Image (tube, coloured by chain):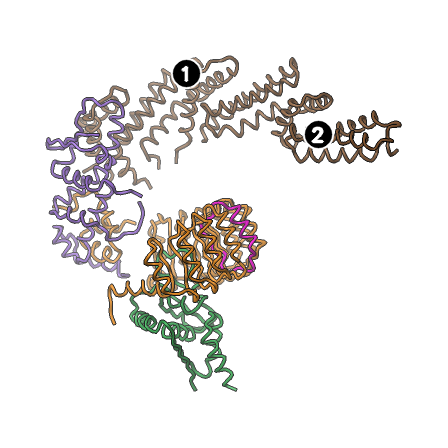
Chain colours: A orange, B purple, C green, D brown
């Protein structure tokens, strides 16, 4: 028996089946052959790494140029100089991810846009001090972008978003949350310039129905996130579901004006709707009844924190919906828990989700290693 | 459906066409070879797999004939029970099964055997890995110290 | 002085064991990074279930549509880490306590997260301070 | 191992496998074996790759002398046939050498990449300069038999199209489009311009419309049969321009003449050909408007001189004209908004300006 007789591909696969700790502290110290095998690299994940590298970033940048994805998650140690030199040493970068790096300024993203145009995925956590000038740099240099995420970046106006929308025609994903100073103009410039868009979200933004209605030009929309958005009437989302036939996931949480008639229209004209979220929507059992009687494709429906939901609506939606597998009955105080228990006992393949039910699931997962 | 394979040592095994189609290499050589009329079902020689390992692979593919293949997912310790009971062999047989799964291009058997070897590696110091795998420590006390220094961030 | 507010409800059994779980740091899927104008980026670990059952805002923020990776980090601003800690303690134990000078911050946080019970408690406390 | 005793066997086996001698599983497997064993002793395979490349280069460059200078019938046969046989042998050779395809090859992060892709690339040492022009002129000759020309060379044209499409640049629908689609389109546009002008010279326009529609359908079906579907939109634009727009002036004149007559069906297929041209209808619209305005004028002028002392007759005549031309708008002009508008305008341009009021 000799492991070294196996080809190096099989040994690399076996070492890839090993965790990082077991590979760097045990596998790399067995022999020089295993050392050279485990030393071989591409995609690197440095997620929060106990914030233990500032200069090691420049060391690994000067070491190898064959990096296609960099994960810089939460990363409180290093400064913009390390990111700049890493961008200088990695032109062939495809995916960039750095969440909650609130110490990075826009010079880092400027150097990134200037020294890696092949970017496809750019995921940028809160990261305050992100002006539109480095964002227009990114928009005008990284034309090959596909995925873009700017979550809770309060320092972004509409200029950078419109510049991003002008270029980067291959943008399939976009997500923005709680980003003020971003209004219907950015949504309109994004909807009419990038027909490749599939995933879009403007949660908590200063967007109204005038900007949401422009999303009908995107017949390739798959998921839509419109949570806590300013005054979105029923007719706009009606037209959205009618035109965008490829819509699979619709998120309308924290919208106090969506009624049950809108839910009925969406369920009727939603031939490809798979996930619908209606948390805090001022609706009643009629919405669930319509979803059950008219929609043969909705699998996930969430009506959490809806005041007027009762036992009858959930029983009828469990009886009439054939594709339903997850019911979001969270904090529906007008719903009896014994009814939910009867439902989970006499309705399989449906995960009724209430407060007590999720607490019970977590308590069973804990009792698997139980205590007192 | 029937296909007759020949091993490296001279034994012949006649099995189902689809079970051999589990092996990408075997189905590729069949589609290239026998799309037209078969020539009296001439034997297919496998000179890189002997008889016992070929029989083990045939048994594994016979048990795994209904698995639906959905390539790049997360790593876990599923390793179904029957695969574990089947891989309860010595190191030589396991390495020969690894070589056969890499030669016959059987992704499932390759994954299961690689996970078994990795679990055999898991939870063992370098000295224990060298003892269980018969690998001489070619590291000097200097080089081993440099290697453990370069990976201090763990 | 010091004010306090205790609540009794149907989850008198689940809340205690969930708080014991939180103190054990075994099962967690929510990470809150609180910052306030100079404070250290305080890092709290908690379950989505209790935070959603105690505040509708947390429930709305936890319904992102995709939770495959399990652990999620939610950065919170505009609130002091001590106020957020007291809010989490109320969410887990149905009981909160505060100083006579920190009632306003607790009330602001509760209004920001729509926790009606402690909102009314802090309103009564601010009325009693006249 | 040893090369002067193993490699020779492998080149001989690849030579066999490049001829449809139908070898048994023992020879496939022997060759595969050879390959595997060679690349097992992480470099090894480089030599073998260069040898494969040399074999393919020599094989193509010394079957080209059989291909150059061929007539623009025989060359299509030769190209189709050799391409078919060669893609079959290329696929079976990629299959023989799969083990080299996945391990020695993964380490390239240059020129050397693949084997089947190699085979295709090398095939561009018998296409780009040698045959491309020749073969494409042959195809254009055949397609130029849009006269009583014969049916079966469809196989040859489809084979050419195929070999150009799969020769779409693998390196590092381009070949098909630069080599063939451009010249094909040019030739088609010239063919149809000559045919159009000749016909519209020695035939009435209202059989030229039928022949243009027939030719448009013909060319759509021909792109369907053996051409790549990518060549549909473009060709359609070209043919519509040639046949319907270049002649839109005689079309306008015949439009007016038909309007004077009652050849409804012809007017209809005219509005059906013209529609396919950007904004070419406006002139037809205004012509219809003026025609039916003059029609209502002449009608009610043939009606009342001292007969305007008859409300009924007047309103009847007006309604008659309106109904006839509304029917003509619906049936012929597909109820187009432009033509309904012209109808409305022209009606509002005779009802209150006639000899019953003047």
Hey, which quadrant is residue D241 in on the image? top right
| Residues at marks 2 and 1 touching, judged by CB atoms closer than 8 Å | no
Q: In this view, does D52 lie to the left or right of D77?
A: left
Height in image: A109 above or below D65? below
Percent x, y for residue D69? 42, 14
Of marks 2 and 1, which one's residue comes earlier in the chain? Answer: 1
Q: Mark 2 points at which residue?
A: D283
Q: Nearer the viewer, residue A345 or B60?
A: A345
Which chain letter goes with mark 1?
Answer: D
* Residue occupying image coordinates x 45% and y 46%: A272
**Magenta residue check for A241:** yes
Q: Position of residue C33 (x, y in %)?
A: 40, 67
Q: Mark 1 points at which residue?
A: D75
Which quarter of the rendering shows the C terminus of chain D? Answer: top right
Single out the mark in the foreground, 2 or 1.
2
The boundaries of the magenta stretch are A226-251
Label 2 Cα crowd, 10 Å radius (few <14 / some 14-19 / many 20+): some
Looking at the rendered structure, the secondary structure element under dot 2 is helix
Please name whichever residue, D70 or A161, is drawn nearer the observer in this view of the structure: A161
The residue lying at 21 percent from left, 54 percent from top is: A27
Instruction: Determine if residue A103 is in view.
Output: no
Distance in Å between CA atoms under marks 2 and 1: 50 Å
Q: Quadrant of the N terminus of chain D?
A: top left
Residue D41 in picture, x, y percent from top left: 18, 38
């Amino acid at each position: 028996p000799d492991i070294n007789q196996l080809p190096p591909s099989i040994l690399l696969k076996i070492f890839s089946n090993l965790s990082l700790d077991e590979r760097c502290l045990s596998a790399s110290l067995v022999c020089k052959y295993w050392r050279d095998l485990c030393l071989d690299f591409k995609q690197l994940d440095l997620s929060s790494r106990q914030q233990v590298t500032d200069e090691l970033l420049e060391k690994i940048a000067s070491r190898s140029q064959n990096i296609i994805e960099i994960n810089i998650s939460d990363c409180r140690s290093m400064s913009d100089n390390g990111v700049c030199v890493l961008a200088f040493k990695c032109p062939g970068l495809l995916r960039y991810t750095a969440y909650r790096c609130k110490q990075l300024s826009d010079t880092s993203i400027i150097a990134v846009a200037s020294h890696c145009p092949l970017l496809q995925k750019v995921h940028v956590g809160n990261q305050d001090k992100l002006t539109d000038e480095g964002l227009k740099q990114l928009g005008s240099k990284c034309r090959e972008l596909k995925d873009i995420h700017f979550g809770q970046c309060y320092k972004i106006s509409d200029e950078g978003m419109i510049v991003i929308a002008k270029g980067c025609l291959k943008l399939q994903r976009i997500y923005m949350q709680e980003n003020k100073l971003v209004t219907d103009q950015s949504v309109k410039a994004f909807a009419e310039h990038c027909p490749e868009l599939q995933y879009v979200g403007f949660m908590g933004c200063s967007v109204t129905s005038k900007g949401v209605i422009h999303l009908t030009k995107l017949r390739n929309l798959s998921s839509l996130d419109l949570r806590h958005i300013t005054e979105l009437d029923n007719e706009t989302v009606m037209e959205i579901v009618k035109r965008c036939k490829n819509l699979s996931s619709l998120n309308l949480c924290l919208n106090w004006i969506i009624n049950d008639r809108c839910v009925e229209v969406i369920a009727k004209e939603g031939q490809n709707l798979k996930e619908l979220y209606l948390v805090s929507c001022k609706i009643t059992d009629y919405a669930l009844i319509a979803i059950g009687r008219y929609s043969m494709t909705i699998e996930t429906v969430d009506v959490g924190w809806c005041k007027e939901i009762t036992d009858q609506g959930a029983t009828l939606i469990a009886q009439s919906s054939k594709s339903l597998r997850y019911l979001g009955l969270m904090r529906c105080d007008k719903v009896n828990e014994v009814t939910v228990e009867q439902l989970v006992q006499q309705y399989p393949h449906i995960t009724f989700s209430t407060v007590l039910q999720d607490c019970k699931r977590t308590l069973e997962r804990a009792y698997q290693m139980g205590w007192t | 459906p029937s296909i007759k394979l020949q091993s490296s040592d001279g034994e012949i095994f006649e099995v189902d066409v689809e079970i051999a189609k589990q092996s990408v290499t075997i189905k590729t050589m069949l589609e290239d070879l026998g799309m037209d009329d078969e020539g009296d079902d001439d034997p297919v020689p496998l000179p890189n797999v002997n008889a016992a390992i070929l029989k083990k692979v045939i048994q594994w593919c016979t048990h795994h004939k209904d698995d639906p293949p959905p390539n790049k997912e997360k790593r876990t310790d599923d390793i179904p029970v029957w695969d574990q009971e089947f891989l309860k062999v010595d190191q030589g047989t396991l390495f020969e099964l690894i070589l056969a799964a890499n030669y016959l291009d059987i992704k499932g058997l390759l994954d299961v055997t690689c996970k078994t070897v990795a679990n055999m590696i898991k939870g063992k110091t370098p000295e224990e890995i060298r003892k269980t795998f018969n690998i001489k420590n070619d590291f000097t006390e200097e080089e081993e110290a440099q290697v453990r220094k370069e990976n201090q961030w763990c | 002085r010091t004010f306090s507010y205790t609540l009794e409800d149907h989850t008198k059994q689940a809340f205690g064991i969930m708080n014991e779980l939180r103190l054990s740091q075994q099962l967690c899927d929510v990470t809150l990074q609180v910052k306030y104008q100079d404070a250290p980026a305080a890092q709290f670990m908690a379950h989505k279930v209790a935070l959603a059952s105690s505040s509708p805002v947390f429930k709305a923020m936890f319904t992102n549509g995709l939770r495959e990776q399990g652990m999620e980090v939610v950065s919170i601003e505009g609130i002091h880490p001590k106020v957020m800690e007291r809010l989490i303690e109320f969410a887990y134990t149905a009981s909160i306590s505060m100083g006579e000078k920190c009632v306003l911050h607790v009330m602001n946080g509760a209004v920001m997260y729509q926790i009606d019970s402690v909102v009314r408690a802090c309103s009564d406390f601010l009325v009693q301070q006249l | 191992i040893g090369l002067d005793q193993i490699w020779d066997d492998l080149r001989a086996g690849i030579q066999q496998v490049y001829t449809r001698q139908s070898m048994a599983k023992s020879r496939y497997m022997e060759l595969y074996t050879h390959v595997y064993n060679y690349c097992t002793s992480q470099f090894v395979g480089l030599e073998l790759y260069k040898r494969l490349k040399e074999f393919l280069k020599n094989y193509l460059t010394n079957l080209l002398k059989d291909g150059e200078d061929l007539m623009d019938e025989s060359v299509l046969k030769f190209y189709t046939q050799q391409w078919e046989d060669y893609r079959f042998s290329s696929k079976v050779l990629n299959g023989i050498c799969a083990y080299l395809n996945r391990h020695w090859v993964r380490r390239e992060c240059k020129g050397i990449y693949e084997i089947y892709s190699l085979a295709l690339v090398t095939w561009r040492d018998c296409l780009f300069r040698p045959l491309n022009k020749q073969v494409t002129n042959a195809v254009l000759k055949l397609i130029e038999k849009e006269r009583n020309g014969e049916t079966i060379n469809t196989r040859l044209i489809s084979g050419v199209v195929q070999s150009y499409v799969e020769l779409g640049l693998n390196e590092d629908l381009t070949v098909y489009k630069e080599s063939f689609e451009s010249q094909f389109l040019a030739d088609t546009e010239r063919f149809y311009t000559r045919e159009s002008t000749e016909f519209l010279q020695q035939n009435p326009v209202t059989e030229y419309m039928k022949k243009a529609e027939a030719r448009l359908l013909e060319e759509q079906r021909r792109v369907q049969v053996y051409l790549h579907e990518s060549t549909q939109d473009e060709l359609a634009r070209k043919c519509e321009q040639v046949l319907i727009e270049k002649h839109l002036e005689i079309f306008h004149t015949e439009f007016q003449n038909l309007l004077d007559a009652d050849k409804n069906e012809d007017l209809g297929r005219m509005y059906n050909l013209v529609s396919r041209i950007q904004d070419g209808l406006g002139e037809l619209k205004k012509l219809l408007e003026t025609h039916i305005h003059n029609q209502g004028l002449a009608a009610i002028e043939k009606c009342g001189e001292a007969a305007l002392n008859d409300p009924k007759m007047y309103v009847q005549t007006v309604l008659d004209v309106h109904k006839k031309y509304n029917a003509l708008v619906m049936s012929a002009f597909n109820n187009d908004a432009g033509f309904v508008a012209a109808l409305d305008k022209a009606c509002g341009r005779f009802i209150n300006n006639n000899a019953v009021t003047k």
